[PDB]
Amino acid sequence: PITKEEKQKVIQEFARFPGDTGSTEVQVALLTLRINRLSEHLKVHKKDHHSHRGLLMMVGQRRRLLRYLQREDPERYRALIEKLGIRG
Amino acid sequence: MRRYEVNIVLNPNLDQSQLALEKEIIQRALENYGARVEKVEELGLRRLAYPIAKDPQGYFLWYQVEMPEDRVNDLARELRIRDNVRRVMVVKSQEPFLANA
Amino acid sequence: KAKVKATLGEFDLRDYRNVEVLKRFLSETGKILPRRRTGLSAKEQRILAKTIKRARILGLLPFTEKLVRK
Amino acid sequence: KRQVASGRAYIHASYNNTIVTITDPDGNPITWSSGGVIGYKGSRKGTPYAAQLAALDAAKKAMAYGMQSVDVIVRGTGAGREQAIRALQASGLQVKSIVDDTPVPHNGCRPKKKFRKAS
RNA sequence: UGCGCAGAUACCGGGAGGAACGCCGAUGGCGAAGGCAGCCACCUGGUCCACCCGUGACGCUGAGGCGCGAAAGCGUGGGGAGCAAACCGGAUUAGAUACCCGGGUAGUCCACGCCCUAAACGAUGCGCGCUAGGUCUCUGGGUCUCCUGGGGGCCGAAGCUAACGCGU
Ligand SMILES: [Mg+2]
Ligand SMILES: [Mg+2]
Ligand SMILES: [Mg+2]
């Protein structure tokens, strides 16, 4: 799983201001968490395809989110992908 | 690390030497895998509804217990290395859904 | 006649040990009784089938019996 | 040859032959009979008469060992069934209890295509 | 046909091994499809509701691309209980390369890799907004006769349709 605290830590390390749960940045972050967990489970459980569709969706939701950010504030985009290491 | 329930059914033909020898080895595994221990229960000698390992009765240990979850399969694998251990059944502890009221 | 829930008082039907209760939800062939006879809800009836099956593995309830007088 | 006082009559009904065997209280065969073991041969061994006859005849052979009472255990469906029971009951040889005990898998091997006409 | 006096069938005890999980079981449930059914644990996907807290149009569809895709089939290596194309026999028939009976290889199962098709069916692409109701049902929530969601069925206003039908 992803225990409530682990999640909570990430919302914290990413929220634009205190009380920020659902901004582009927190959202991208959380997906990235889910993805890396889900990807570790996939390098082992290669034949679990139903789960793998979940991935494709998360990877999309992410690119679609990031696409928006790069179009509004190309700045905190560059910062966010650096703080995570992605896309480029 | 979550809460569980380890049931063991044992050989119903033991004197206190054999009996508590097994009961100790158990406490070792339990301990040697991360288990702390809330309640114990020992109804012991009960008649099974069909004979397990040739034998119309069984000795019942039940433990509620908390432990590292990624080891609970390992624990139980070791619990039945023994021969006087006949059934080992481990189960996620649970809210007790009731009925009639 | 009676539904097996109409009989009892309150009980934990997540409790795979209480054979004194759980034993009443079986036929004389020790088969899990249908809803129409258990008087239970779809949801309860689901939970029970589970508890009954767990009992069977511990040795406390039967998988089968034989019909007496046919 | 020992005297048994009581024990088991096993009836094995089928849509092709009824067969009956009698045993001591640990299930060891004393005597036995079947449709073919009386005269009938081919498709008559199923008929409730064939069943009755076989049944009765087995009981007579057991009564030779002085058999006085039995628990009946019946297995399978077929024409001779209630008739082989009705027989043992009316053979003198006293019927203590009855019990169906037909095998049934909890979904085991693939049945032969004849038996999945219920496909 | 076959099997059986090298003692079968039927019965009691013990063991070995493979496949599939009775009752629960539904008009049920989950999944995008194909599809998913003993019980336990771990790892993991989707989804619904309530609160109305956060972002602030970040949306819909989607040629090509990629991935999934029942069954049968193919390659290598296992496994093999029951069932069974082909095949070998017994029947039936005017004949019977069939339907019925006795056997039986591939295959069905597991590992890894291919194939990529179907009455792959709701024969109904995906999304959104609008337009009477009644009834049964799964799963939520509330102030729990009932109300408010989300799913599953039937009947049917308006309207539609060659018709049969469809009809929140
Ligand atoms: Mg295949
Ligand atoms: Mg092959
Ligand atoms: Mg054949």
Image (cartoon, coloured by chain):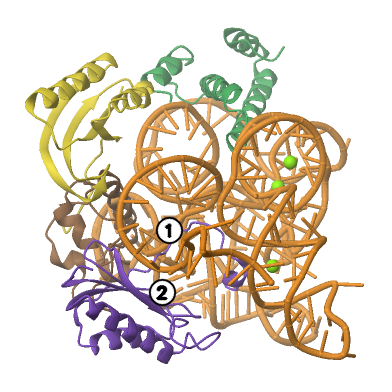
Chain colours: A green, B yellow, C brown, D purple, E orange
Numbered circles on residues, count:
2
Q: Secondary structure at mark 2?
A: loop
Eyeballing the image, is B46 above or below E78?
below
x 57%, y 28%: residue? A45
Please state the horizontal and vertical placement of residue B19, each as a whole percent of the image. Answer: 12, 27
x 62%, y 7%: residue? A82
x 23%, y 35%: residue? B7
- Discs 1/2, front: 2
Tags 1 and 2 on a common chain: yes
Ligand 1 neighbours mark 1 (CB distance < 8 Å): no
Q: Residues within 10 Å of mark 1 (few under 14, many from 20)?
A: few
Quarter of the figure with the C terminus of chain A: top right
Eyeballing the image, is A61 above or below D32?
above
Relative to D62, is E148 on the left or the right? Answer: right
- The mark found on residue D76 in the picture is 2
Eyeballing the image, is A13 above or below D119?
above
- The mark found on residue D106 in the picture is 1
Q: Residues within 10 Å of mark 2 (few under 14, many from 20)?
A: some
Parent chain of label 2: D
Relative to C46, is E47 on the left or the right? Answer: right
